[PDB]
Image (cartoon, rainbow, N blue to C red; front, side, top):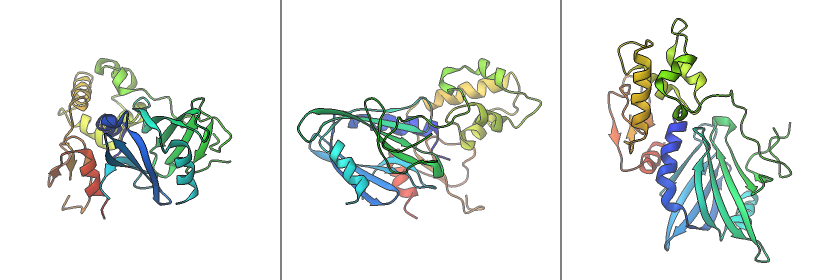
Length: 266
């Protein structure tokens, strides 16, 4: 769950330099992972897309089965027209334009949904007909016949579409695990960020909550601080800003990709 919406917003920002690049290679080093090399001005870049139930994520990194095959068929060759996030959700869509077998142009979208054990990687056409799924849902259906439909959802709100003054409407201060309430109403939030906001004033009240919220959402728009963090716990975490919850120890990095490269070595 530390791969948030907001973390996603920031990983997507750093992947825009790949727009225009050509999909040059696609491997699958295990059942949970797609490695997609994008060649932009004659240099290669390794895009890792993991669907792993714990480690689901999207990053560039540093160091053939059916699904990879299907992917090469439709994508190998193509140009990346767009990489974008759906709302503030934990969903990235890469838009590729390519050729089929007999040269006619085809329009494809790769959809990564990062939801712990409900993580999936999915290929659809320009009309959202699912071409293939790294995982199938039979019992929403996620099979090659069908139209892709977004995840369940609780009709949450996009924290970017709302002001702090406006958040109040959705908070009962008397209730009140303010972080838990913020997690329940806002798309792409996590414990990390909810706890952080609640931490940005001494007390959570109708005057302060708005201030905290705005303050934090403003910081999300700044270029991030890729940061690794407890010697008491043994625990490890990562994020894209420094969180008053992060004392004690912490290493920061050049990029989120570096940050991740390290963190998932163990």
